[PDB]
Length: 233
Ligand SMILES: [Ca+2]
Ligand SMILES: [Ca+2]
Ligand SMILES: [Ca+2]
Ligand SMILES: [Ca+2]
Ligand SMILES: [Ca+2]
Ligand SMILES: [Ca+2]
Ligand SMILES: [Cl-]
Ligand SMILES: [K+]
Image (cartoon, rainbow, N blue to C red):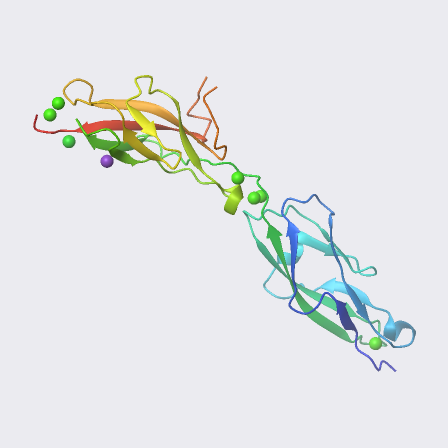
């Protein structure tokens, strides 16, 4: 007679497992262990995921029915999905029906630095540069505006974004702070030169410097255009 139900020993109920994202196929994740103190088959334990809920996170993993080893079955990308919900099942092999026990388990992916700062180009047809405007004859240091649009898909210190002029301001009309603040250096006159164009690099490298620059293919770059607003002078 099948007296005992299997009892999970590991993991503990409600534990959130933390693994690195982007670990290769069939990487080892966890050793599940449940015990059953019954005689022979009534006390043999077999491991599975529950696959009958609407939650299909089980597709990312396998569990060995005998050893309880969970391995990865697919790419684990934290930027695609950060948390994965599994329901562990431990079954004995009882007479016409086994007793089974279930234990929810969450797996959370720790971020790695596998993305760089990238712009997204305005839709085809509309101008491909970020536009900034300043009054002509603005004094030295005047905020022209904030260059922006570059995002790093990583987390915290893996997602630092800095902006740098890559090319196009040989006259030193502007200074670009690494935070994206674009400032006036020189006296700018609408009635002489009313428009400026140059290229900015977004980088996580605080000490990036210019080294051939293709704005169609390289989304770490964008064009910035500055126009001077009219003063009555
Ligand atoms: Ca049993
Ligand atoms: Ca990733
Ligand atoms: Ca990054
Ligand atoms: Ca990442
Ligand atoms: Ca003027
Ligand atoms: Ca004017
Ligand atoms: Cl204007
Ligand atoms: K402005």
